[PDB]
Image (tube, coloured by chain):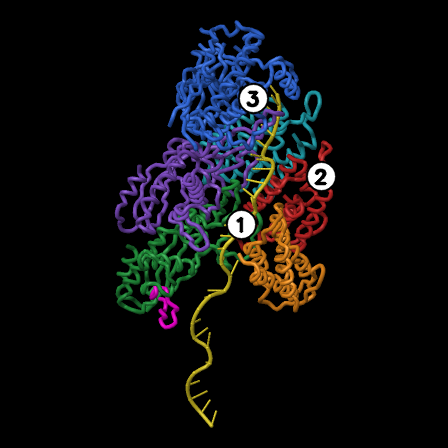
Chain colours: A blue, B cyan, C red, D orange, E purple, F green, G yellow
Amino acid sequence: MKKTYRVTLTALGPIFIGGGEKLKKYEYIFDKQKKVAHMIDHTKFTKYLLEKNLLDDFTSRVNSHFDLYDYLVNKKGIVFMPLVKYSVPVAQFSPPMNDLNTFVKDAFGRPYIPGSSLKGALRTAILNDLKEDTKENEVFAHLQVSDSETIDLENLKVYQKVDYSKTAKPLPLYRECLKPNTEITFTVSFDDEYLTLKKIQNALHKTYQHYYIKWLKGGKVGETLIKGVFALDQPSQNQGEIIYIGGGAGFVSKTLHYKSKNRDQARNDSFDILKQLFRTTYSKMRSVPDNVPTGKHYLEMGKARIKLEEL
Amino acid sequence: TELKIGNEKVNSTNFGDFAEKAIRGINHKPFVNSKGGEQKITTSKIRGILELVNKVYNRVINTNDVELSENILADIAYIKVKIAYESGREPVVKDFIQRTAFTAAITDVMNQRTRESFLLFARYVESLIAYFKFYGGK
Amino acid sequence: TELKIGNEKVNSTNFGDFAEKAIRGINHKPFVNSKGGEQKITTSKIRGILELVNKVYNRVINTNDVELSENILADIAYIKVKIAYESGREPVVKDFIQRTAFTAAITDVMNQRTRESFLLFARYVESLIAYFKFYGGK
Amino acid sequence: TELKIGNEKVNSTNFGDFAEKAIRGINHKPFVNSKGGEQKITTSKIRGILELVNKVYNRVINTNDVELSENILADIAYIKVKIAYESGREPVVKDFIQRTAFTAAITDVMNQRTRESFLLFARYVESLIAYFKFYGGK
Amino acid sequence: MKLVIEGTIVLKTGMHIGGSSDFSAIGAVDSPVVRDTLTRLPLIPGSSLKGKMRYLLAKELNNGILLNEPNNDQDEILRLFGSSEKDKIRRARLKFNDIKLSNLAELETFNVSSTEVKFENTINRKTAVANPRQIERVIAGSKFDFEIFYNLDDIKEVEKDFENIKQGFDLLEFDYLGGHGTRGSGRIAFENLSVITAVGNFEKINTLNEILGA
Amino acid sequence: MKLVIEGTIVLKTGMHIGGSSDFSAIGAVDSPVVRDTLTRLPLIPGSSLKGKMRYLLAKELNNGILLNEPNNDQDEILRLFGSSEKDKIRRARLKFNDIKLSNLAELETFNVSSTEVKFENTINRKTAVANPRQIERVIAGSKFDFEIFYNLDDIKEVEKDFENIKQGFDLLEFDYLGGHGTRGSGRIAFENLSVITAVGNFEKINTLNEILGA
RNA sequence: CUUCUUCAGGUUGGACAGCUGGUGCUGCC
């Protein structure tokens, strides 16, 4: 019989998931004076333009660039407050904002992680057993995963994506993210007959072990150990409470074959499957850490915790 | 119901045929670049343009109004901004937009300011893209 | 009432037999893939085409008007655009359209503009789906 | 008269006997499905055949032309298309359509193009349903 | 009698129910929602609500084992929802109605529409190809004010019927109403549940409210 | 003397009345609505309105129960709807008419037709597979102006006749008219209920209006 | 300066299908 185990999402790391995209700074301000960033609303901007320069004249002055940090307060000399909805501070560790990614957000501004996104995440988590039941399995087709609940608006903080391969070189794409120590809640319930609490505990424990002891230690020790350590504490072995929720973290969470193989064998299968994708050879999928304001702390974008409570 | 892009555009028996002949004229004489012609503008430039037109169209369909609101007009203005920037990025998008009179259609629907002209223009652009995929590929 | 499927005029009584001929010809000699393979058009795709025809037929049929108005002709031109899009996307759909005269039939309806012409076109497409279900199976 | 069936000939006097023979052949040795059979067609599946035939019988019962009009012929062809379509949906229907040669009778009606031929065909179908009644049920 | 079960259903996550008959565009929306034809407002079909309630109530009243034909269920389900069982044909006590969107005013003040369009994915771990779709979902935060009529065939069968109706409504709470419900959509909540008599007054109608309003 | 009962029937939800004469395609409609053959305008048959009103009123007036045969209903129903019993024939004091929809111009102002298409399905509880249908349905907001003829035979019990007429009308308001009513469809409303004299004038005609409008 | 823009299944399925009553009486050779 179905039961109710309420679950929360203490997203200690910033999150990214796809719901759309936006181009260069043509409707958002990327300030650099006090290191903050801004995103515009719609209706107030429409009224503002109606009570100001005409829309065709607005259009006719785009020749790339068209930066909104040096125009709205310099070429116009007006306050930007009526045209910000989730304004956000920015701190980066230096290649300018080439492009910006958009987390999926419902019609009320607010960000959330939709359904079937958590279903793909729990597929790559709990599908460690077999690789055949992806359409007809009751572990999800009888499970009822729901959307995420409210994700805070005061916890937004822009972050820089960095490289891990023996140097911390910034990468062109930047993105506003969610600052740490933010707590999100869910209402996700499930049954017992084909998704058992002991079975799910065993599944999470075995996936956690096959990630940490099998793959993660080899990657951390393979190239550089002192790169993470400013702290890189990464609390571990705590009953498997680690979730790579979201995206922009790595290709390991996308492909699930290295949780049931050997390091050399899993990497051989990965090489075989990645020969069909892209033309660059690499031993492993390099990480994309960030910088938090200063304490140079590298944290993988999209962490969370798992806990279950009745009702 | 009536659109002006220079060739007496009509909602009936006119939008599909004229989009098809514009696509054929584009393909009949490939764009000339440095130093080889036939740039083969992919769907990536054509999409995105379609994506903006269709997000505005999505917000328009669930609105039973004879005239478009100021929000929709600002959306069309932002459409024109995006198209101008993308055309300025590389000349093949300039050729595609100029030959198909995308900007002329935008200006005409901005002058008419009615939902009928906007739906006609969206139908027209979808016709452009459908006939591009029919007579082209990728 | 006199459609122009291909090079042979289609009247109001031979739609079923000619659609049966079209389906059997496709079934007997089917499309050959680019990668040395054999496959037909799926039931989902032809059902979607019929749905497209059902979208306009459901509003045309509840009328006594001799000639279709400008809105119906606009929807028919849009359906022709979507036919072109489907043909350009999957080559099997293009083959299915070309072996029949589904594009030529829709063009004949667009040129005739009468209600009875589209009624015969709907009959012909319905018979195409019928003989796909009968011959192709499921 | 002169209603071809495929193996015999039903004239205006000989529809009920052939209908009872066909129903007995249906009642004897029921259909064989994937699971060895064995259920028989439902009253509300020969329903559909009966209203399909009546939808033209009502329009032909009250007239005096010897030959059927182009509107009646189109509807008879559409009945043929429909009976072809629905047979592909269910096998327990297809055996009914085959063992009782509906299609040959419809084709002969479409070839004779006379009022009396279709009246004889409708009488045959009506007798067929009447004889399915009093033998089966449900 | 003609008891009238009023209430309100609110969506916690965006709900999708299909049934449109309009031209889907090339990149606009691949699957819109069911809406009223005249007012263009999002609609909850009372057939969808009735069917999902019959499924959920029937399965929970069948020890979580629902396998029978609709006409082959327990007596109470049939006497609330109707059945054409050959001899004892039962008329549906519950008369569900197509529920129309109600709170357009507050949504309008919120500068939001009653529907949104979501892009999710169709990605694959294998040869990397994704098939993007466009689901239109009624905005979360939508209220649908409903009126479900009721037939009081016998006074003995009123409190049992109404407690079963309340538990059927509260079984939907830990479930969805329709559409792509297995994938995070369709969560609904019922509020302002009550009942009134259409004509005259009924004895012990407050017993119905105390088991339907709480 | 004879009286004419005017009024309007407004659809609250979609309303489907069955009856099919020709050309049901295999992907478009599976159950069309009854229509006026000449003008193609949808209509409410007087048979269906009379039958539903008689059923509801006979059930209400008798005991709340109604299992009998129409020619054995109560005396009010017998005298108002007729009786074909051999030795006891009551001539009907009501003559229902077929009711075509009147506000088609109002509907065309809103750029909609008078009929919609409703997409339903049934889900086999065994395999969870859906079987779709396609119900044509007259859109909500459609208005049907009607006329019922009342044959004023007994000058004194006309008041009770009209009270029962209003009661049956109000029973219809808390019920459905035609088609799949329990699954959302069929809801209607009555307005502008006014009785007028067919020829001449009736003494209690201002009384018969105030027992129709109230 | 990339990469798909939806794909694959169910298109209605069963239940009733015309019942009851009158049914040429009166006037003339």
Marks counted in the figure total 3
Task: Name the residue at the top extreme.
Answer: A226
Residue A254 marker: 3
What stretch of residues is rendered in magenta?
F77-92
Q: How many neighbours does mark 2 have within 10 angstroms: few (below 14), some (14-19), or many (20 or more)?
A: some
Residue C31 marker: 2
Q: Along the horizontal axis of the image, is A3 left or right of G7?
A: left
Instruction: Examine the image and state in which quarter residue A44 appears.
Output: top left
Marks 2 and 1 close (CB-CB < 8 Å): no
Residue F5 versus residue B110 in the image, above or below: below
Instruction: Confirm whether residue A85 shows in the render.
Output: no
Query: SS of the residue at dot 1?
Result: loop
Q: Along the horizontal axis of the image, is A152 left or right of C8?
A: left
Q: Nearer the viewer, residue B128 or C24?
A: C24
Q: Chain of mark 3?
A: A
F130 in magenta: no
Q: How many neighbours does mark 3 have within 10 angstroms: few (below 14), some (14-19), or many (20 or more)?
A: some
